[PDB]
Each structure stands twice: as structure tokens, then as C-alpha cells.
Image 1 (cartoon, each protein chain N blue to C red):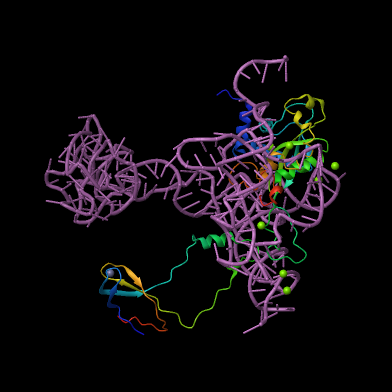
Image 2: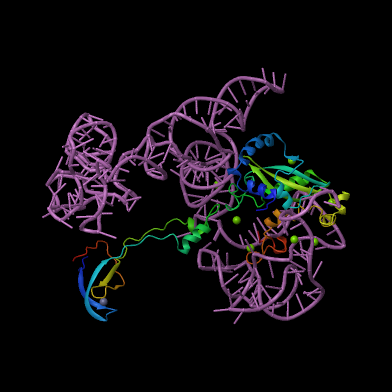
Length: 196
Length: 92
RNA sequence: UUUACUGCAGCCUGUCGUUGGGUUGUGGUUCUGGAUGUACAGUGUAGGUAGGAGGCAUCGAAGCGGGUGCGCCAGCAUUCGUGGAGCCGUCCUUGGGACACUACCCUUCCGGGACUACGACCCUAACUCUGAGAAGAGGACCCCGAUAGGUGGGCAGUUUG
RNA sequence: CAUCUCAGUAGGAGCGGGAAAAGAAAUCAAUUGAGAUGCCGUAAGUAACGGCGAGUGAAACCGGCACAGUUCAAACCGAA
Ligand SMILES: [Mg+2]
Ligand SMILES: [Mg+2]
Ligand SMILES: [Mg+2]
Ligand SMILES: [Mg+2]
Ligand SMILES: [Mg+2]
Ligand SMILES: [Mg+2]
Ligand SMILES: [Mg+2]
Ligand SMILES: [Zn+2]
């Protein structure tokens, strides 16, 4: 079958535990642990996924590995008097996924760019790693572009901290239509947050 | 307090008087698929849980004797309002 | 305040992940050498069972060995021989099962090799501590995320007609 | 009074414009149909939940306001 090499990379990352990618994981995890919270990397770790999510090789497009802990929302026991249903907090995991946390940290680190998408790249017993694709709206190469000039608009500022990314809309309960989405569209706030 | 193993009594299905066999009604075990059990699962979270943290209730000085009269022709049982006795021999 | 009712933190322990490479004892999983299948024996070893029997055989078939799969040191296989016929059974050892080659598909045998789960031991490369660093010391344990059970006036909400 | 209610309310953190959010079916229907989204009316205090107590509580069909559809990834060419 006449197939592109993106297909082969996709297949290789389809089942990481049963290919050559496991050894590469073993080497890469050490170097990744030595690094910081947010790091700029020249090339994406998985080319096919990045191209699928809207990555091109031009100026003004940046890619970054973020580092986020595992587990639920670490929550404090209430100091004062609750009612025995609000008193417990150890089993109460959060309401925000880990991709959203990763993208928000990346946005906080880069004040001039704007988040586009992200994807899963690895994980171990203490950490998870994602890569976030960032686009610069004030670069002339982006402005001339016809498939990316929508980001040079006054409604795309802070695009990641208002739940407009793909993971944000997954977490808002708006990944589908029909039954079950009675109280999740066009927004959570519109229904007094009884959805989600 | 004795009662015969067999005797002759009206059968509501055959609509005639004929022999019956008396036996003891043994309380079964509650299953886990009835809607009360599903509700108990749905209501277990953090803290108190309403009906499902109720303390078990007391008991009465003497229960009733629960008996089932099974016919010997059609094999269809029927139940009758039950009396209250402490020691119940079953005198065949 | 407490051995009042209901809960929640903290702590103790099992399981899953992080988490790798060997030493062997475990059990099947899985695989070979023989239908191993044999008491009323046998000329025969129920070549499971079984067209209740017909093809093999100096053009290879026998009684015996420490005994060759194995078992009743009998004897179907032809194996290391040994004599140089065990033929089918309509002479059925007239059967627990009565038996003949293109069938053993299957009592079984089980280097049990093989991935697996357990108990113990060893190794370093993950990981942890110390150091500016070389390096040193531990080590797949601990910490950590999740889940299950306990103890728990440390703390919370209430009741005490 | 403990589940429930008060209520996702009061309060907090982040982002942000003249508006914002949503938006072109892996949809709703029922036998056979409709054809992106938002807002108003109705369905309806109905279905559903609940010491089945107190209470909480929709959507689709249907009528209106206003109407608008498209762009990438890949298969083919390989710097055009
Ligand atoms: Mg930071
Ligand atoms: Mg908009
Ligand atoms: Mg107290
Ligand atoms: Mg109160
Ligand atoms: Mg501002
Ligand atoms: Mg959208
Ligand atoms: Mg409510
Ligand atoms: Zn009767």
C-alpha cells in the first residue's frame, strides 16, 4: 500500500509498549526528568500528531514540553464547621483535566503567543508530559497566511484560559450533540453550572 | 402448640375440600439487583447516607408462625393469616 | 467531656502503577518417547473407545534380558539383541475394557522447555541520599498516585422527649 | 436533624470585547420524516429524582426573530 511515513510513525506510537518506542522512552525519561517545568524543543516528538493538529514549519510557530504531576486536586481539610458531606476531601478529585493544566501553564509562561493544541507524549509514576503548539499572531508570516490569520482577531486573546481549545471543549461537555448535553451548551455558566 | 401435618380443608383453586400439606415459610435472602440495592450503591459517597446508615431496629416478644398450605392435587400453595406462638411443635 | 449517634483527618496493612536482569522450589499452562490400554493373563498389551473385525510377516515376525514405552522382570513393538512367526479372531484369554495395519483425535508420558502468579536469594542501569564535581552508600525496597480493610473525641455536625 | 434543601447561591482566582459564548450532525425521530447555531413562546410544575418526606425538575415535536456556509491533515506532483 502506497503509504506516507507519517502513517508509519502513527503505527509506531499506536502501541508504545510493544515496539522500539519503549527503549526510547527509557532513555528519554531521564533527560526529561532533569529538565524544568516548561521547555522549548525545536522539533515535535511525534510529527504525525502535530501535523494533524495544525502544525506547519514556519516562523512564529513554537512547540513546548510541559510537565504536570499526576493525581487529583490536592485539597485541604476545611478548618471550620462543615456538614459531613462537605467535610471530606481526600477522595474528591478535581474537575479539571491534566491537559488543561498543562496548556494553562504554557500560556502563563509565553505572554505574547497563543495556544493551539496539545497531545500526550509520555508518563511515569510521578509526572505526565504534554507538548503544546503555540503560534505568534504578530509575525508577518502568520499574517500573510490564509489558514492561520483567524488568530489575528480580538476574540482569540487568552484562547486557552477560556476553554476554547479542544481539550477545553471536551472538558466543557461540548464534544457531542443530543442527549446528555441539555445543560452544557452554549456554556456552563448559562445554566447555573448544573452541567459538568 | 401442635398442628397436624395433614388435614382436609378448602382449596381456593380446586374450589373443593381435599387434603393439604402444611410446611414452614423460611425467609429468603435479599438479592443485590433490586432497585433498593442499586440506590444504596448510588447513595454511598462521603459521610452520612440517610436510610442506609440507620441502626437496625429492635424486636417484639413473640413473632408469628408463618405457614404455607400446599394442596396435594394441584400442588398450588396458599397462605393464611398467621397466629402468634412461642413454642410451635408441628405434630404430624 | 465520653465506651452517646453519624462522619472526617492522621497512622497500620493488602492489591494495582512507577518497575528492570538472573538463581532456583512451586503448579498447571503447554509438548514429546508408547495407546502407554495389563487382573477371568496373554497364542495378544482392552493398538482407548471402535464398521464386535482381516491388513501386516526371512519380501521381518515370536516368547527373553538389568527387563526397551511400560506393566503382573508376562510381552503386543522390531528396538541393543534373541531365537529365526506374532497373523485376524467367524479358537474373541467368547471381554470392566476383547483386542488386527492409513492412525494413539484422547488412561498417559509428563527435558515439562514455554508467558504467567507465589516465597527466598543475587546483580545494576531506573530511582533515593550525600558531595561543587569525580565519586560514595542504598536499590527495584522506600517515597509517590489510586483503591480495600482496620484503629481513630485528634477534629466536625447534631441529639439527650 | 444527618441524606435532601439553602445552592453551584454568597465569596474567591484567571482571561476578556463592544458585545461574548455557541455553531455547520458519528443529531433528533419512528415505522415512511426533519435538516447548523443562538434567543423568545409552549410542552409543564409533566416525565424524572427524593428520610418516595419537605422539596428539586427537564428536553424533543410545534410557532416566531434572524439567516450563510466553509477551511486544514492524507492519498497525486516534490521547492514550482
Ligand atoms: Mg511555575
Ligand atoms: Mg465568537
Ligand atoms: Mg464534639
Ligand atoms: Mg444547623
Ligand atoms: Mg487586561
Ligand atoms: Mg466552535
Ligand atoms: Mg439544585
Ligand atoms: Zn388444590
